[PDB]
Amino acid sequence: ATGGYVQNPSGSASFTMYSGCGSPACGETASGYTAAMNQLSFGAGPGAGAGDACGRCFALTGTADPYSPSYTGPFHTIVVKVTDLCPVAGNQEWCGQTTSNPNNQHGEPVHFDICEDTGGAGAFFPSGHGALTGTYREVSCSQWSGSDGSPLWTGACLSGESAANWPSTACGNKGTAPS
Image: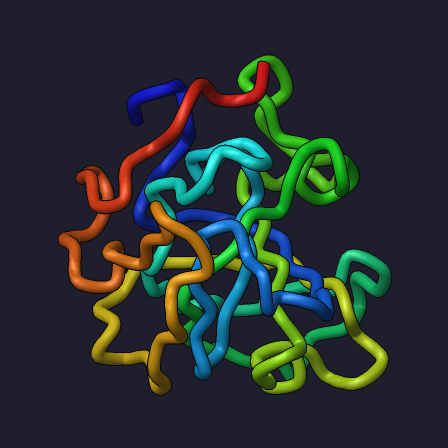
């Protein structure tokens, strides 16, 4: 996509959880399940505002535990709305994908950090299994439950929630992908 960001509607991803998404990079929260996406797919660097992932909805499916290969389940599928950025500089292990090294250390090209604040992390991760790998696919936000918060600053954007799936432009990417 423009800027060199990697924005495919479906593929492989890794998954973790985080707490604290009340001031997210898209500038607007949501009450349903939400996630941060690694910088190279989010479409903006830290402090740059909303990237083109903002507001888009994705079905996330766990398929493996990277710390226990023998674990065969149970896993879950949830639908999240992306509201936030998982930056290279703050989380290299999972979100360090760059144009020069497009996979994270766990071998995945995309990462979703699922927010605990609104329950998505508990819906997705079995207790005792807080990091997973699996798949993602962009879906209609009709499959997502919840409602959006109020914009935190001028430029806040979740307009990906009504856009056609990637490849396409809703909020738009900002700047250039991390190198």
